Amino acid sequence: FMPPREVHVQVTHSMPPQKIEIFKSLDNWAEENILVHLKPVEKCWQPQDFLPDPASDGFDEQVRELRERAKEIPDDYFVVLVGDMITEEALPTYQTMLNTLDGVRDETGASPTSWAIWTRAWTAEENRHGDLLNKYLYLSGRVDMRQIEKTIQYLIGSGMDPRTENSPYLGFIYTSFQERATFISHGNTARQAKEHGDIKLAQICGTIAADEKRHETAYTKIVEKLFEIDPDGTVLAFADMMRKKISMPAHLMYDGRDDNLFDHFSAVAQRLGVYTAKDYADILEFLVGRWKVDKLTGLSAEGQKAQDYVCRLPPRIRRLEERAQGRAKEAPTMPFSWIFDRQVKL
Amino acid sequence: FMPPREVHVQVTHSMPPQKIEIFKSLDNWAEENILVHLKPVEKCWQPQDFLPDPASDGFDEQVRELRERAKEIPDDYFVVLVGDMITEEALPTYQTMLNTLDGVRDETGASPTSWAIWTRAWTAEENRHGDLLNKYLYLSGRVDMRQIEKTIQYLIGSGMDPRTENSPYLGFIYTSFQERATFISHGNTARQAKEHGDIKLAQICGTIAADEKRHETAYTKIVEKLFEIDPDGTVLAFADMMRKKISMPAHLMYDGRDDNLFDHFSAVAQRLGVYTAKDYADILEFLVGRWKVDKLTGLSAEGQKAQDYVCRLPPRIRRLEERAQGRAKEAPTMPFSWIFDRQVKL
Ligand SMILES: [Sr+2]
Ligand SMILES: [Sr+2]
Ligand SMILES: [Sr+2]
Ligand SMILES: [Sr+2]
């Protein structure tokens, strides 16, 4: 029952180690510039806001209306939706995954630093995506809660290696990308829920999309500041992430029945257009467009090489990973334990 | 709407910094001696095992029997139960809280080290206490899910400072105690559930108690090994935790209506005997008895002082915090937001 590890060696602390001060200093800055994309807790939605209300006479019809509506949502949609849920539910991983980042560490789990206060606060805002999506799935009864929960144990136990190497540079570039990635996914799970006739589910995806949107604003804004304080090394770390490929935080997914779980899940995301290869390019393309890496000047010989790599990459990815729709045309039908070994088109 | 921080200054890295090697070396040891108190995922229970089964014709009666049964459980019990659930739900915090501990860090979120593999794996086993206890509360409809969810946002956003100061010594002593603490709580929530006539809920606490039991076995076993490799400093760190008081991982609890949430919750835990001050002493007493700190010899002048402090402390706590039951006799009735501003005896 051997789960997956990743196939790359360990790389810890791959950043000039004095540079903990670039971030030490930016403490006040971050307070004024990131700690505002915080909605105060008292103004945030919570999951209860979208699920049947168990302390109302309405509870019964609400659960029943829920389940009826979910019958009209097809099995493939559910696979994708479950994928997302599990990713989201693996949250403790990502709080650790920001807390490995060197300059912007929490040091005591309650550190008064601006970075930490943001970390705790971001985590807190993300942790309710889990609750909501899970309670929703549990109620629909369209999916096998027990396998889904196991996959989660299997995921949290193995974490992920997104190859940030404790670098606040690399990290904040990664999240920037990954956060937009999830917003696009959740955006389409939403649209599509709507088109299948279940607005309440759309609204659930809709809202979650909308949180990530806010986080991507924050995260792009830390990387943007670093393109001013260190144009050389920030392109250098951005070119570094792109060679490495951005591997989504759930690549180690294991249900105990499938060695290509992630691969297979992703095939379905792709087929339904929830998160295609196409989309992948646009995220990089947006990021080059947004960070104005395009317009940077005075770079070292190694910096100039990194720029023209990153800039003319989206065109390339678009094509070679075009011909991976011409692989979703005549693709096999295959079971997923998450839906009781029923079978969706891969 | 200002939440609580803690009233003690920051103390990071308070352990002789070469000692990362004592733990680097103990890697093989830990593999043979801690990574066995791991139940392989495929053999673990998941939350679905204890809740109504939504993809079964049974679903409806099972939810209905659940809620009927929870009407027979009183409001005070639920406050305590909720306390626990929120504590458990704040999980991401504790993964971070082990990952600050110096010698035994995860360094990339997927570190092949034995300590890390145990950390991820412990985390994974604990994260289902959340799912389960939450789903159960949600279904009962006896409590206000939206406040409970907010408290959790308020908790995760502020973390905790249990005063371990990145010390694997201090940390592992702390968890050792705190893990026993939760086992005793969960134990009584269980017994009491049973006495109020709800076996299924008892079984839920029962199981969770049973996980913590295993974890305390593991954690006591790391501290016991340190009483062999460093008798001096491990008593010194144990006497250090006891002067500091062991402040449970939810002390910063905030619902947005109550500045003494934690105090007040705790009052109720106490009143029902779910986790008293009495209990507190027994955990220390058990720990002195189990670690044989009693029988240690050849300590420095500072070590000998630390021993006789820790040894004759349980007697003391027992008495002075005896007369805090004669404060639960004629105590006020007061509302909790978690139960719709209904009123339990504090
Ligand atoms: Sr959760
Ligand atoms: Sr099932
Ligand atoms: Sr029902
Ligand atoms: Sr409500």
Image: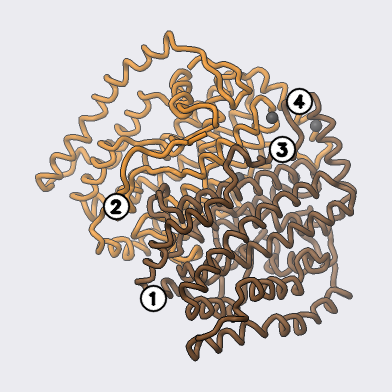
Chain colours: A orange, B brown
Q: Quadrant of residue B53?
A: top right
Give the quadrant of the N terminus of chain B.
bottom right
Q: Quadrant of residue A105?
A: bottom left
> Disc 4 marks which residue?
B56
Badge 3 and badge 1 in a common chain? yes
Give the quadrant of the C terminus of chain B.
bottom right
Q: Quadrant of residue A342?
A: top right
> Disc 3 marks which residue?
B49
Separation of marks 2 and 3 at Cα, in angstroms: 49 Å
Chain to which the residue tagged by mark 1 belongs: B
Three-letter code for the amino acid on which mark 3 is drawn: Asp
Badge 4 and badge 3 in a common chain? yes
Above or below A299: residue A112: below
Which numbered tag is attached to residue B16?
Answer: 1
Residue at coordinates 62% horizontally, 39% vertically from top-left? B43
Three-letter code for the amino acid on which mark 2 is drawn: Lys
Left or right, residue B272 beside residue A89: right
Q: Is mark 3 within 8 Å of ligand 2?
A: no
Mark 4 residue element: loop
Residues at discs 4 and 1 in contact (Cβ within 8 Å): no
Badge 2 and badge 4 in a common chain? no
Which of pointers 2 and 4 indicates the residue nearer the eye?
Answer: 4
Separation of marks 3 and 1 at Cα, in angstroms: 46 Å
Residue at coordinates 81% horizontally, 82% vertically from top-left? B323
Which numbered tag is attached to residue A225?
Answer: 2
